[PDB]
Structure formats: C-alpha cells, structure tokens
Image 1 (cartoon, each protein chain N blue to C red):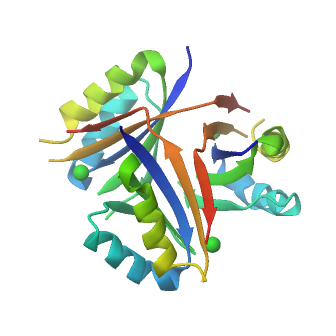
Image 2: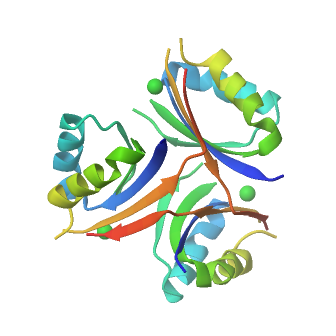
Length: 77
Length: 77
Length: 77
Ligand SMILES: [Cl-]
Ligand SMILES: [Cl-]
Ligand SMILES: [Cl-]
C-alpha cells in the first residue's frame, strides 16, 4: 500500500548502465558510496519486483547485493 | 517509545541552512552524499514531526524527499 | 530467522581497526561517509549481538552510534 527503501551494492562497472536503466523505468535513486557503488532508491511496494529485476538484468552475474527495507512514512516537500 | 531513522534528500543550496537549524534543535545528522545532499538522522518517535517540520521550513519549495524508517534497536558505545 | 541492517557512526581513527576486525569475523560492510565514518553492514539476526560487540570492543570509549534496522528482504544476484 506504501513504500520500501531499496539499498543496493553493485560493481562500479555496472553503475553506469544500471543507473541508466533505472531512469528509463522511473526509479529515482541516489548514488551513495564507491570503491563497489552503493545506491539507495525509494520504491513503491508494487514495484519492488520490478526494480529487483532491473538490478538483476544490469548487474550481478558481476555482483549485486540488495536490501528491501520497510518505510513507516514518506514525505515530499 | 523508541526511534526512527530519517533519510532525507535535499538541494545542496539548502544543505548549509538545514544543517544549521538541525543543530539548533538538537538533531544529530550525518552528511552522506551530494551532487542533492543526502542526510540521515536518528530521531526519537516524539520528534519526527519536529524534524519533518524543520526540513520543511528550510528545504523544499527548493526540493526535499524524506523517509521515516523503523529502528529495532539503538546503541551508543 | 532473517536479516538486519546495521548502521554505524564511529570515529575515523577507529575506522581502520574496526574494519579489520569485521573482516576477521566474516562481516561484509560498506564505508559510507566520513568527516566520523559511517558504515553499514547487513547482518543475520543471530549475529547482531556479535557485531555490536565487535563495534564496541574496537570503537567507542572514542565514540560509536549504532542502528539495528529491520530488513524485509535480501537478494544476492
Ligand atoms: Cl556485490
Ligand atoms: Cl529533492
Ligand atoms: Cl559517535
């Protein structure tokens, strides 16, 4: 009914292409840390499977680690 | 009875002033990533509305995106 | 039965040694932000007490702040 926080660690050489395909599927993600790049992206419940699948197609093999975390509340100001 | 993790994405030109006013209201936040600056701040349940309001007054219009996330446990060592 | 996300803020002069001893106890952590270094580390329920204890022995006194957060789902690709 509501949101999840995705936290993803992936290979930097997939950072470019993953980021590109997030954009194409209307996912708004933030680049957090590299060496391995960490992204976090707020996603609707409906669309977790969707973003998992995108991360999967563009990353891993390559490597990828993903956390789906609960969100109590979301505000845009 | 307990805590929340706030995760906030805001405009970098509001980073300076938001950070200042967090301090004034005894909020301890960490600067995480910029381009848009990401902050996270551990807050007590009681005080979520408070920190939302601060983020709101000093950021957005400007833009701001905020996640309130559950915390199982908190330790200071 | 499942996982937690640990989020830890500690002193940078303990960053070196904490990181070393995480590795020795098979904890996979990501370095996020410094000034104070922020780490996050995905941990199994079983092993929270374990990683708390490691953070504690190697950090704080020194200072350390730790969040244990719920994880709905975990995927490796
Ligand atoms: Cl990985
Ligand atoms: Cl924004
Ligand atoms: Cl600290």
